Length: 106
Ligand SMILES: [Zn+2]
Image (cartoon, rainbow, N blue to C red):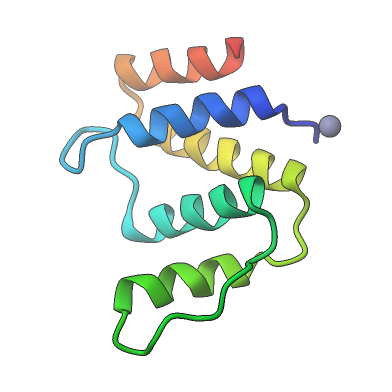
């Protein structure tokens, strides 16, 4: 399905806005999911070599990004936005409902 860059950009702003400790909190796996589609949506296909074995954080991010090689920016937009909507719906607070509404109106 069609997803606009504008809705992606709003989703990114929201994701970046979330505190590490809060009622709306992506899991570790969900943050990797956001990461991989964020890179794929903006940079496109992974364009660097895998970090060294002892760069635990860096190599986990790289692996995620590499795993979506070949995905179009538009699918990346869609997957990113949809993951945030999933998370907001699961959080199910008046705050999360407001975020859903902002994405819808973007
Ligand atoms: Zn489209």
